[PDB]
Image (cartoon, rainbow, N blue to C red; front, side):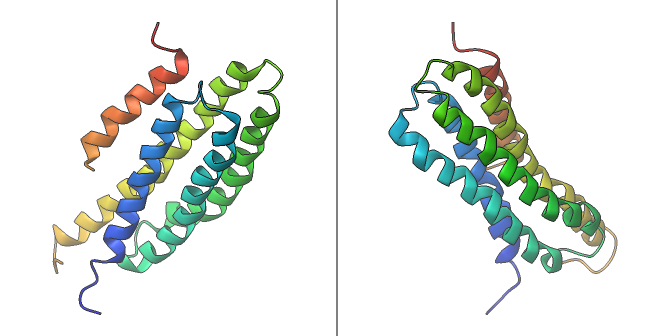
Length: 161
């Protein structure tokens, strides 16, 4: 081991990667074939599951002060998992019939809150990191993700003409 700047970057990294997929899939969600749906869920499922561990190590990596939301985020994360995979699992069966675009719209909505949530996790605790530094005993961009999230919203409302 060397420094304690390994886990701090790990979580801040995963929180971004997962977002990249959330939007990507939302783009080709329509044309999303039945062969890409199987693995698709596996991708999102990994993000949420990973987030649980990422935050776990974030506790110590950050100064005790923002554990409130972090704690509630743990149990909450689990629920979001079963909830997400649940609805998504339905679309996989309600796609061969005809009502695909329907479940697709709502589907994106769910993943939308998840993507932003996973990111907000580190964003929130971030305020604590500076709280200690800018006071005493000191120790993939924000805007980039913001703009990306915006498009995701519009993509859900409806396709490009």
